[PDB]
Image (cartoon, coloured by chain):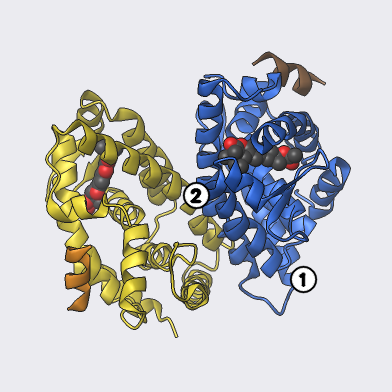
Chain colours: A brown, B orange, C yellow, D blue
Amino acid sequence: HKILHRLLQD
Amino acid sequence: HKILHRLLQD
Amino acid sequence: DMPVERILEAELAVEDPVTNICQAADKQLFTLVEWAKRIPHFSELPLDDQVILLRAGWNELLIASFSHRSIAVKDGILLATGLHVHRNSAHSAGVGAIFDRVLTELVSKMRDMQMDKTELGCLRAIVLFNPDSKGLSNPAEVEALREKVYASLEAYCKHKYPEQPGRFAKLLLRLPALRSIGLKCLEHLFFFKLIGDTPIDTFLMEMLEAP
Amino acid sequence: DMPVERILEAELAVEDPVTNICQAADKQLFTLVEWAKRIPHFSELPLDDQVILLRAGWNELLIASFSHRSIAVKDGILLATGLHVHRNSAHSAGVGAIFDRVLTELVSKMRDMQMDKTELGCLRAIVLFNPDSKGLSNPAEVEALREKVYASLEAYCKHKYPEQPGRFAKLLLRLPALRSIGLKCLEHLFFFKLIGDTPIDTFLMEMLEAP
Ligand SMILES: C=CC(C)(C)c1cc2cc3c(cc2oc1=O)O[C@H](C(C)(C)OC(C)=O)C3
Ligand SMILES: C=CC(C)(C)c1cc2cc3c(cc2oc1=O)O[C@H](C(C)(C)OC(C)=O)C3
């Protein structure tokens, strides 16, 4: 789930 | 819905 | 008025594994009608609205009942037929995913909080008085009855469990789980009907009819 | 601690019709992540649990938001893209049944009770902190946060609306409707994806991925 992870990272 | 009606009737 | 005493009375008055489950479901549908008649003010609703409410609510109502019945058993459900369905048996019949949801989201949570029979009865009465049910001649009347149930349930919870201020909300917040599980159980039932190699008795079959 | 002030802040910080709806959904998914980061203690959960919670909750979260956004409009929904979807347009696109459910079970009910933004935010925070979400490394931690939200929501309701003792329960009892509507909306989304003649953007598409 790359988009979600990236957005949550910061 | 004959069964339900009959059972609710009494 | 909506006394929790009358709601508990109603609960106490009525007290392939897929096949056994479906047979149990049909059996309990008869018992469900008698339960509902014992819920204060239900019998005084128009007959067509009684029909709508039970047709809308039967699966969640039955699911709540067998889930609470199963709190003292590990990795299984107790059917009203006296039959036990083990997690393993459910899994081996291809219905493991939904069975596990019942165990984790309902049974184990009812067990964890020691949901009592009055609370179960009230939750079931709330489900029964579903004002969102399509076709109701007077939704406001059904909304009113639901309000009376949860007013009474909260009072019961505050009096019986004053040490647990969040108990009332905790009870209500099992209802979304019950709704989703009910919907998935229905999906399976429609599939069993479609496939045709699971016996479905007359009352259960009637519930799978269109409005 | 779970202050309703911080939850309202989060709400205020983020403030073929099927195509427009899907485009709006994708857009709002980005905004949803930012909303969740502003919900107290969410960011301090393991990253994998943040992922699980948002993947489990996104549709209900988005549905709650557009439903409350639409309370001042008749027979329609307000998308965050600035676009309005009229009941007639939804019906004419073959999505009338689910659209009508949103209007009757969510929008009209939010309108009837004048659900405020703090209450909406708290309901959304409850949805977000879903301890039934599969794969959570610490469900008890998520359960704890949900408990904190509904403890705070109730306190808010008792203070702001002392004349409505049943308001708190009334708010929580929209959650089963939100759950069922969310599930049906998801079913439609999977169908639009399957059929292939509705553009679905990357984040929305990612949400339709398997775990
Ligand atoms: C195992 C899951 C599946 C999906 C097959 C499934 C289960 C299921 C279980 C029960 C039911 C209907 C069901 O429909 C289903 O599709 O009503 C029966 C109860 C309420 C137990 O009656 C008694 C005896 O109390 C319980
Ligand atoms: C009309 C119903 C159907 C079934 C087609 C349907 C509707 C639907 C609607 C919205 C959605 C996903 C949806 O999936 C659906 O399948 O997220 C969009 C919102 C939350 C509005 O983003 C904004 C702009 O706030 C709203």
Whether residue D57 is visible, yes or no, is: no
Q: Quadrant of residue C31?
A: bottom left
**C193 left or right of C83?**
right
The quarter of the image holding the N terminus of chain C is bottom left
Residue matched to label 2: C176
Q: Quadrant of residue D204?
A: top right
Secondary structure of the residue carrying tag 1 is helix
A2 vs C12, nearest the viewer:
A2
Dots 1 and 2 on the same chain: no
Residue at horizontal 79%, vertical 33%? D31
Q: Name the outermost residue toward the bottom.
A: C1
- What mark, if any, has residue D159 been given in the picture? 1
The quarter of the image holding the C terminus of chain C is bottom left
Q: Name the outermost residue toward the front.
A: D92
Secondary structure of the residue carrying tag 2 is helix
Residue at horizontal 49%, vertical 72%? C139
Asked if D100 appears above or below C138 in the picture, the reply is above
**C191 left or right of D186?**
left
Give residue C191's position: percent from left, percent from top.
Answer: 27, 34
